Image: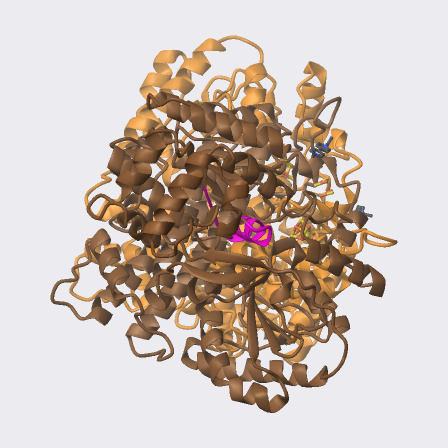
Chain colours: A orange, B brown
């Protein structure tokens, strides 16, 4: 049972679900085995009606597609479409945020406003939008219009690419034609070139995929920018994680998905419906988070992290989850069925993301408070239906210190050097106190036992003084196993890393160290790491592919994770992926994505499914980057 | 051997290829069997790294995806992505045309110009772009800017949707939220909603797919519009089809792909290099067409149709094909390999479409004549290498009368009624002389013996007085079996259809009838049929779903064909598809796409793999539409 998840509460709820005959994601995975060898090697194509075409990894015919598409062509086309799908997800997230900001500053959504004036000003200056002597709503409208225009061809390339990376990096990517012209333009061109009879050259397809991954990076950066403008830039905050944050005597409302435009309003309206909740016979409206919108409200408001990714269903298995408010992106549709057994009202709110069997509430920024009142009223009804009945909420919760936006990190460092905030960090990088930086990102994969790779690699990296930051469900796993709790620094961190964390934390008025891992936010907030990594780059006069910075999609599952890893490579990072991507069916594509892209961008993928070996490989990558700079290791 | 193709020349070249051990598409198809039952039923998903997930069509587990995605959800997501890929192809085609027009009228491409002033004026009037008292290049620039803007969100919806269908049809599609906001916007939203954890409601996904199919329709209409502005609106023309159009004593240059922006320049520059060809020891530069760019030059310049679709390789099997100029879209990459055995120089010209092993010439409208001179010089070299050596060009060619643009059709009808050109056609529809209209469209599929479905259904429809028009490789098949030759009217057409064709042809100054099938152009020129079908709609005061008009993707292969069939349904047509699409794995999705969409758009798919039964079903659909109007049948 410990082979399905390393989270103890998840094991408890798996026992409960097995008890009651509630089918789980691990059960469905067990029904799916043996899985198909063509697809999970990437050697399968259904790109037209002459298919499906499978190419045996080794042996006799079939060796080539019916139309003549080779193994590498098929592999590259599939990977390109994965990158495009992830880019579409992130880009639509940011597109909805841009629409919300425009509507707010045009007077069409009064529940939304400019909550971070300073970030709006700095973004407008970064884009060349004039701020001085201009109405705040005027420059916000201009910023939203620039964001919307970055989705198509225009006078300029994608500004959320070209103005967020150092100019030398932009030059390197422009010398290879990797700079995107428009986000949706790149997505459509990927869909065009990978369809039948089009592009059939592996190197060409992989370069196009790098461009599409940069479009995804632009989408992530824009989403972070607009969410910070509308809802505020996160600052350090203390909260709790895992299922134990649920309360049998409260109205449990879990916000699940990626777009915060809805759940941020939920967090506010719930406090106003506190009295209504009391009238129902409840202590209050206990709002918890699931997946990335949960991480957004965790970073901005200290909302507890109920659960993440592959184990989302386990929340409903408590029996005390009265509402699950879904927007889109990584909701298992199984919840809609599982609700029937758990007395959970599952509520979709977005037009392009509905699930069969769930109540739908058509969200609109013009009626966000109205929608939220209706939804939480349904949640109150659901609580009323279960008064006095038995629930099993595992009494398991960790302490989580989060809210480490790049702005907050720079400020906390400025406590040690007011005029050159990055200098203390670079100093400790030089003297060995900080070996390097690792970004943990991505989701949980049902094939990898939950949180095993993240915790294992994190332990091996922290004991060697790697400054570890995390986002999304990587942050979720590490926070559910105690890595955002400073009380574990002594157990987890090496001496130099402990000293650096202690120095910053004691300079930041909390008497103790920073938590062993810095939670940088959601899946799109990976852009935050870019913002940090580029900044240090600018401070050191070098390109990212010269920094001892690595990334780890240790348990990657989603197409967005593939796009994120691809643009982590593209901006120049060594990027470990801890699950097998569908590239092993063609040695040329694997060699390009792990070896020869070093000649193109300086980054490269590291495919390794053993977390001990993967941690050693990440350590070696960090140490080679250190050596290239002339640093001991 | 007749089981692989009904084209006699193709059978001859298949015998030659088998003789010499040249692997063919039919051979590769034979290596691919048995094909996978999950994919060709649509019951397979690889939309994230937890897959591949297969759902058995019948029996025990696996019954549901690992994440809980049902059979219908998986089927709808796959079909949605197919529609998006086809839309991306057509839209990128039209996008490149828009860029070429803008560059031409800004002074950046002197080889391109406004060749149809009248079509530019009428398009500008249809869009509300003011023509009166404006420079032709100014309104052309405005038209190109509107075309480019239709690819993203703006003040208005997609104008190439909303201004080309009758306003009642636009109202019907707007009542269901089917009107696209932007072409690339819709494509990206399809990629977003079909990725993991997003949309999981079959009806929702299919409605989104209808919207994306309308985006594809807009792309087709825009491509036709811009190609007509730059290169001219086709008029009737006489030429020849099949391999016999190749000449052993000429420099054989075959233009292959979809975008005419290149091959139209090739057609002109070749005549200027005629003297160079003579110097090489050749009679001239024999330019032939393959697939849809070949059909474009056939409709505009009377360039012979060498071959189409699944049999393209057979051209190289003649041994006398010296050059194959590929842009993109439906080129079998096998040609790049097959060239090594046939002495054929295969030349890619587009950045996003290269093939491993082929010479690449970077095309640019700023250097189109320069590129063309280089490419045809390589072709002359290739001819020089083969002087006096043996070739086998089958002496098989049919007569093809084509160039039937909607403008040309309206003019030919105006010969019978100068002020109400559509009235004679509607008159003969009423009195039974014309039973209905069938649009043949789409490609050849290696599973269906080549051209069998097209010819069979065409015979059964023509003998019952259906006015038959065709595009793309449907036109290619029907023209290679003699359906564009008026000399066959007596053999093919029923008495009333023969009388109508004879009346129009004798009124049009050629003493004989029109050909049994009206060639309306390329794959995007399906929009032409829309232009006709809408026009009659406007003349009759009814919606398309009330017209006795049907469509037939009789041997569909490409994702573009799926998108085309979907928007044929969406605008309200009964639409037969003659190959199995990946929808039969879910009865609900099949029922929606064949039965209940009648309540939504009035059109519906007809899935039938037997061409006799399919022809009967098309006949019955035409007759039901006749009955709804109160007409005998
Ligand atoms: C022959 C087709 N095929 C290729 C690869 C695998 C596979 C790869 C990695 N892992 C995790 C170690 C498991 C399975 C299974 C099947
Ligand atoms: C069980 C999986 N599966 C489903 C359908 C077919 C199939 C369908 C139609 N045709 C043409 C008549 C051939 C095969 C084959 C396999
Ligand atoms: S595009 Fe090629 S490999 Fe893919 S299904 Fe079609 S014929 Fe097979
Ligand atoms: S999205 Fe669902 S059905 Fe598709 S591969 Fe992932 S888990 Fe399987
Ligand atoms: S045959 Fe298994 S993924 Fe296609
Ligand atoms: S298992 Fe055959 S298409 Fe995926």
User: In this figure, what is the number of numbered marks?
Assistant: 0
Q: Residue at x 33, y 22 (%)?
A: A374
Q: Position of residue A513 (x, y in %)?
A: 55, 53
> Left or right: where does residue B310 sit relative to residue B3?
left
Identify whether B332 is placed above or below B85: below
> Left or right: where does residue A232 sit relative to residue B202?
left
Q: Residue B68, located in which quarter of the rendered image?
A: top right
Taking the image as drawn, is residue A355 in sight? Answer: no
Outermost residue to the bottom: B279
Question: Is-magenta flag for residue B413?
Answer: no
Q: Position of residue A354 (x, y in %)?
A: 47, 30
Q: Position of residue A343 (x, y in %)?
A: 52, 15
Q: Magenta part mainly helix, strand or loop?
A: helix
Question: Is-magenta flag for residue B476?
Answer: yes
Quarter of the C terminus of chain B within the rendering: top left
Q: Residue A27, located in which quarter of the rendered image?
A: top right
Q: Position of residue A436 (x, y in %)?
A: 63, 66
Q: Depth check: B630 or A510 in front? A: B630
Magenta region, residue range? B468-482
Identify whether B382 is placed above or below A161: below
Q: Residue at x 24, y 54 (%)?
A: A141
Q: Residue at x 72, y 23 (%)?
A: B58
Q: Depth check: B487 or A543 in front? A: B487
Taking the image as drawn, is residue B31 in sight? Answer: yes
Q: Depth check: B513 or A365 in front? A: B513
Outermost residue to the right: A59
């Amino acid at each position: 049972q410990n082979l399905k998840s390393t989270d103890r509460a998840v094991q408890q709820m798996l026992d409960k679900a097995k008890r009651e005959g509630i089918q789980t994601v691990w059960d469905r995975y067990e029904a799916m085995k043996p899985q198909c060898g063509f697809g999970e090697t990437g050697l399968c194509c259904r790109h037209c009606l002459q298919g499906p075409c499978g190419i045996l990894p080794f042996g006799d015919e079939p060796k080539v597609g019916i139309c003549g598409a080779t193994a590498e062509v098929i592999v590259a086309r599939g990977l390109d479409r994965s990158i495009a799908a992830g880019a579409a997800g992130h880009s639509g997230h940011a597109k909805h945020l841009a629409h919300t900001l425009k509507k707010a500053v045009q007077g069409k959504a009064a529940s939304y406003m400019i909550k971070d004036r300073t970030k709006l000003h700095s973004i407008a200056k970064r884009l060349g939008i004039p701020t001085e002597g201009q109405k705040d709503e005027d420059i916000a409208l201009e910023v939203a219009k620039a964001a919307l225009a970055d989705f198509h061809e225009k006078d300029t390339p994608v500004l959320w690419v070209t103005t967020v990376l150092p100019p030398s990096r932009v030059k390197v990517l422009s010398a290879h034609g990797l700079i995107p012209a428009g986000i949706d333009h790149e997505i459509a061109e990927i869909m065009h070139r990978t369809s039948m009879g089009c592009d059939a050259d592996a190197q060409n397809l992989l370069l196009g995929g790098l461009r599409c991954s940069l479009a995804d990076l632009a989408g992530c950066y824009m989403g972070t920018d607009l969410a910070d403008i509308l809802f505020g830039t996160p600052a350090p905050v203390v909260t709790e994680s895992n299922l134990g944050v649920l309360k049998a005597d409260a109205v449990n409302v879990a916000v699940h998905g990626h777009n915060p435009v809805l759940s941020d309003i939920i967090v506010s309206v719930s406090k106003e419906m506190e009295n209504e909740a009391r009238a129902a016979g409840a202590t209050g409206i206990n709002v918890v988070g699931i997946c990335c919108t949960g991480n957004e409200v965790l970073m901005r408001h200290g909302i507890p992290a109920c659960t993440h990714s592959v184990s989302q269903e386990m929340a409903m298995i408590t029996g005390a989850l009265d509402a699950m408010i879904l927007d889109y992106q990584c909701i298992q549709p199984s919840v809609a069925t599982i609700a029937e057994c758990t007395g959970t009202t599952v509520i979709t709110t977005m037009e392009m993301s509905k699930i069969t069997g769930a109540t739908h509430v058509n969200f609109a920024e013009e009626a966000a408070v109205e929608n939220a009142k209706q939804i939480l009223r349904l949640a109150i009804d659901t609580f009323k239906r279960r008064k006095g009945k038995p629930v099993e909420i595992p009494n398991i919760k960790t302490k989580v210190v989060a809210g480490f936006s790049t702005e907050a990190i720079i400020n906390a460092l400025s406590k040690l050097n007011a005029n050159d905030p990055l200098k203390p960090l670079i100093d400790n990088v030089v003297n060995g106190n900080i070996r390097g930086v690792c970004l943990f990102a991505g989701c949980n994969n049902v094939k990898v036992p939950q949180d095993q790779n993240f915790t294992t690699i994190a332990r091996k990296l922290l004991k060697q003084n790697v400054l570890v930051v995390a986002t999304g469900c990587g942050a979720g796993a590490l926070m559910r196993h105690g890595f955002m709790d400073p009380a574990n620094v002594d157990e987890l961190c090496g001496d130099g890393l402990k000293a650096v964390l202690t120095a910053i934390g004691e300079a930041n008025g909390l008497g103790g160290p920073l938590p062993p891992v810095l939670h940088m936010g959601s899946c799109v907030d990976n852009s935050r790491a870019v913002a940090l990594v580029a900044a240090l780059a600018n401070r050191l006069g070098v390109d990212l592919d010269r920094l001892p910075v690595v990334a780890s999609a240790a348990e990657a599952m989603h197409e967005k994770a593939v796009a994120i890893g691809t643009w982590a490579v593209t901006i120049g990072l060594p990027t470990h992926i801890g699950v097998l991507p569908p590239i092993t069916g063609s040695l040329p594509v694997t060699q390009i994505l792990t070896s020869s892209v070093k000649d193109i961008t300086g980054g490269y993928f590291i495919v390794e499914l053993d977390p001990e070996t993967a941690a050693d490989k990440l350590l070696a990558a960090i140490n080679e980057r250190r050596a290239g700079l002339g640093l001991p290791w």
